[PDB]
Length: 82
Ligand code: HEC
Image (cartoon, rainbow, N blue to C red; front, side, top):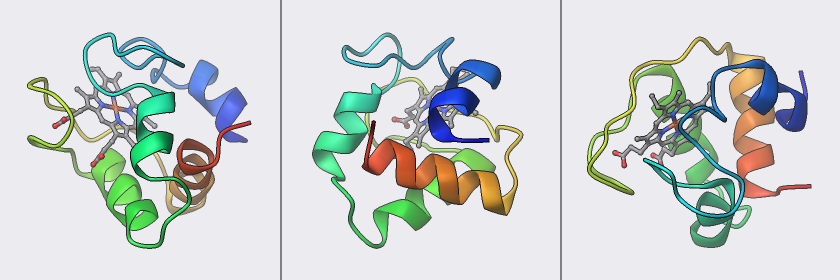
């Protein structure tokens, strides 16, 4: 259930990367712009449940399979990485 095991178990590493951008934003890019800030955790949690349109690059993201407890652990891991 942790962000390191959920990034490899769920289909997030297919489009996203750990350092450089592949098609959308990378884990190092979302942590550099939003480094543990209130408001960004709610926008990143609502973006994975509904979808993002024009924020990091030209490619959009569809609504991924994630619950309220998984969106809070994934939002806190992308803001503060291990
Ligand atoms: C390719 C089909 C993707 C997969 C699979 C996942 N994501 Fe994604 N994500 C993708 C793009 C192209 C973008 C940028 C969209 C834009 O308009 O710029 C994103 C963005 C995110 C974000 C940031 C949202 C924001 O800043 O508002 C997060 C937090 C994010 N993606 C998370 C995420 C997770 C947890 C995934 C596995 C369940 C996942 N993404 C898969 C493209 C793709």
